[PDB]
Amino acid sequence: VLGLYYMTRDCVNAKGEGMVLTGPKEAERLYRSGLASLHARVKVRITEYE
Amino acid sequence: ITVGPYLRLHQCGLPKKMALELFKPFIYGKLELRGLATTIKAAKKMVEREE
Amino acid sequence: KPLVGTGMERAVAVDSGVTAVAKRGGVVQYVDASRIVIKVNEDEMYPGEAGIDIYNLTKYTRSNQNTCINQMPCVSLGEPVERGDVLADGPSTDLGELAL
Amino acid sequence: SVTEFLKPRLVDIEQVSSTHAKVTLEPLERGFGHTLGNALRRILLSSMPGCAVTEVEIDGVLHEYSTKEGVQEDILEILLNLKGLAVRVQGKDEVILTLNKSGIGPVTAADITHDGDVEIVKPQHVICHLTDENASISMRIKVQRGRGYVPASTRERPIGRLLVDACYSPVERIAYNVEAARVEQRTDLDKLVIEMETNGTIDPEEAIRRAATILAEQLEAFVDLEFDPILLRPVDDLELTVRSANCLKAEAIHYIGDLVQRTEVELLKTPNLGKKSLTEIKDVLASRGLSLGMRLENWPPAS
Amino acid sequence: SVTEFLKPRLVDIEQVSSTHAKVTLEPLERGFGHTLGNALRRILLSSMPGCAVTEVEIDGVLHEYSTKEGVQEDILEILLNLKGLAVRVQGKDEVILTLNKSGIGPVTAADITHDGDVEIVKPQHVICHLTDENASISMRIKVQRGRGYVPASTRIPIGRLLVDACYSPVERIAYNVEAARVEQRTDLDKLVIEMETNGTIDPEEAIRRAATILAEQLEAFVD
Amino acid sequence: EIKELLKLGDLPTSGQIRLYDGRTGEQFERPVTVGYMYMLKLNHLVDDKM
């Protein structure tokens, strides 16, 4: 619960704030390489199934 | 009991020295089945020696 | 020894009876991993007596819980000791301080 | 250019002391500093070969839970002291050193009997003390080469020989740092500094080379991509009579296993086989420790 | 017997798709699974040669947050669609392409002006949508060659809209370490790698090239 | 007094340092508390329970 709470939060003016991503995979690729923070507020293209 | 963080939801971790004692008659039957021990005493001795 | 203690270690260690404490002062005449022989000072000696104290240490004896009881010397050859000093460390003891 | 990685070289070696050293690798393209450093640290910590003491024998003692007259340390503490002796064996993978001492005083590593191949790097290493004038100690110390950590329990011996746990790794600790490399006309190159603390028995350059060799050797696969003998004796080994043997060969039973697997009811209904012959067959089987009605899987054994 | 280490024996490959693979290696010495996996992952994420779109220019649009009539989507959607374009370049290290299309429907990758030296691996990759009948889209696309990933915010004319550069052909790489045993030795490692590329190169080639790149960095030390 | 003693030994006053991951070499995102504690071994051995 602590880990899932820490990863799913937002911070004001983090590293990589305001950029646009083409999906979750690009988000993971950015986070692993250190270019963006886990709390940055971005705009991501998401596909959901109903 | 300790914690295994790698197990899946239907799995538990059992020490093998306990499993040898608990499942002994099944081991006797399996040893006899494939011919490794023609008699019960041979299988008992083989299990005792822990081959 | 505990790096952070409260100062009650020495009282518990000495007042427990697991460490060999000198009965009289003097100089360590002979120290060994199994015995200690102290040459008592002249003024504390009784008349008509060769003044020496012999301390036999207990080595690897069994306790009520099947643990080990073993005393180790903690003094050097030919060094002064005063009445009340600790000569051997019992189980869970470091230089007369309780150490669990 | 676009696909041309500058390849690091070993540039500088600094010897702060006998057990402390620094190594410099330069140059490094962006992102390779940590990539090389962490792998090298893991390999150096885990898999460096060395030499260690594995057995001891003292003349008067029988086990490590005793004490020797004239010695201030228990035998267990003497073994714990010998566990940390830093040796260097040059030619062989095994050696036996001898120590003899007498008289009041400390017994240190400088008192080990001299030998050619074996080198002691810490002559001041205290082994024990002698507190009696007419007291002596003499011991045989077994040293051998290995890697990792092999406890005594995991690995008959005469009474009086004492085993010791073996810690072979010479490396005590490794650290590393990445700095800015001042190459001629670029500012996007890194310099790796590896700080190494050992026990003095391995040279830093050979440690680095061994770690790199292990890594490159491991990196190749990626660029690439019983029945019991009595059951096997022929049935004619049994001393069967003529009629029983003819009946059995009339049923195509040539090995002991095939006869064994037949149940008694099946053999009762065998033509020309009277009950007397069946009882005789049971007798000859029971003489050797077998019975009719067993069950085997994966038969015949393809032979 | 002191300089010999265990090496993999069961290299199993499972292709979940044409660009998604899972590779299993076992057995390995204790702790080498993490070393090899992390080294390969860092190499494949951070440093891999590739070719990608860098900047764009559309005549009708001056600033990024403009609005182009006749196009169902918006400008940032067009940039996101372009960023995912997978192109192989063989001749040079800097090319220019142009897309001019009019009508109604999906403007896709197959409509880009065909150039022999360059190659598009997915002609069916959507670029944009045209709604009005009298709607025409004209744009120029610049492709360069590089390594890894370069955000557009690092490099800060008119209409020269910057696009994040993703040169490395790896879409996603992950790894895992499990327990494996030989008969006697039971504390061994097994390495599992799961990776997806963009279609320019197959996963096996990506792993081979990463291993080659890492192994060429150790030449000055290997005996 | 604890903070003064930490200052005397040239250690951070807050009592938290920066640790690194042993498997990936990557710094943990937040400072971690490191120190020395006195541990005991109680007389409940698994050799007896099994």
Image: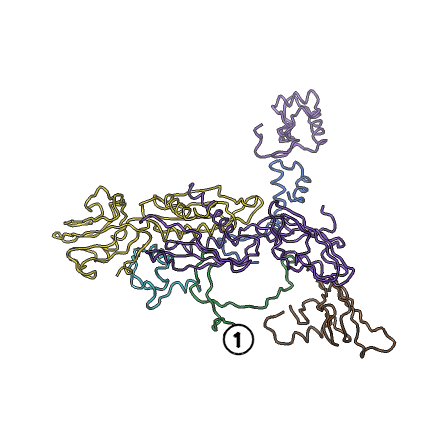
Chain colours: A cyan, B blue, C brown, D purple, E yellow, F green
Query: Visible in this render: residue C19?
Result: yes
Identify which residue, E63 or E137, lies in the foreground.
Answer: E63
- The picture places residue D182, in percent across and down from the top left corner, at 37, 58
- The picture places residue D226, in percent across and down from the top left corner, at 60, 34
| Left or right of residue B39: residue D43 | left
Q: Place residue D251 in its image quadrant.
A: top right
Identify which residue, F23 or E221, lies in the foreground.
Answer: E221
Quadrant containing the C terminus of chain D is top right
Query: Visible in this render: residue C89?
Result: no
Q: Amino acid at mark 1?
A: Leu
Identify which residue, E201 or E5, lies in the foreground.
Answer: E5
Q: Place residue D276 in its image quadrant.
A: top right
Q: How many numbered markers are drawn?
A: 1
In the image, farthest residue toward the left: E134
User: Residue at left 42%, top 51%?
Assistant: D9
| Left or right of residue B49: residue D225 | left
Dot 1 falls on a residue whose secondary structure is helix
Q: Place residue D70 in its image quadrant.
A: bottom right
User: Residue at left 41%, top 55%?
Assistant: D33
> Which residue carries the number 1 mark?
F5
- The picture places residue A23, in percent across and down from the top left corner, at 31, 55
A5 lies above or below E130: below
Q: Chain of mark 1?
A: F
Circle 1 crowding by C-alpha within 10 Å: few under 14, some 14–19, many from 20: few
Identify which residue, E93 or E105, lies in the foreground.
Answer: E93
| Left or right of residue E60: residue E210 | right
In the image, farthest residue toward the bottom: C43
- The picture places residue D200, in percent across and down from the top left corner, at 57, 55
| Left or right of residue D292: residue E158 | left
In the image, farthest residue toward the right: C48
